[PDB]
Amino acid sequence: MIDNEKVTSGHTTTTRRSCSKVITKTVTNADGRTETTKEVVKSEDGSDCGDADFDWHHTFPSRGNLDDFFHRDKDDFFT
Image 1 (cartoon, helix red, strand yellow):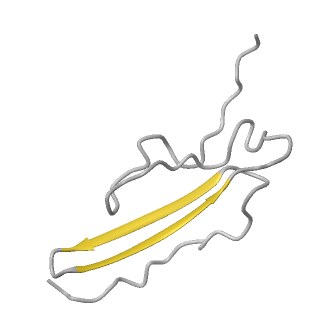
Image 2: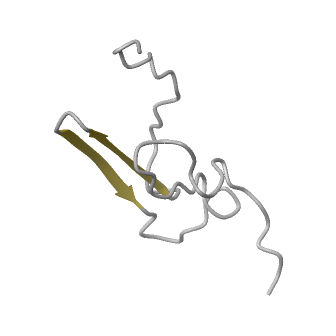
């Protein structure tokens, strides 16, 4: 119903790399259409953002959850 993409309000993100940021949105429409938006950017230096990694992401067919937890942030205990 409502064949129209919502306004999709969101920070739209801006910084990538300094923190782990992976954006994959794959839309499969049984009508025969298929678009794939993929953007993997992982800090190539250091690798320690948000006390570990800002946002985790994962790989969903279209949308539903990150199989992790957005805004991830916690102390890695102490080896």
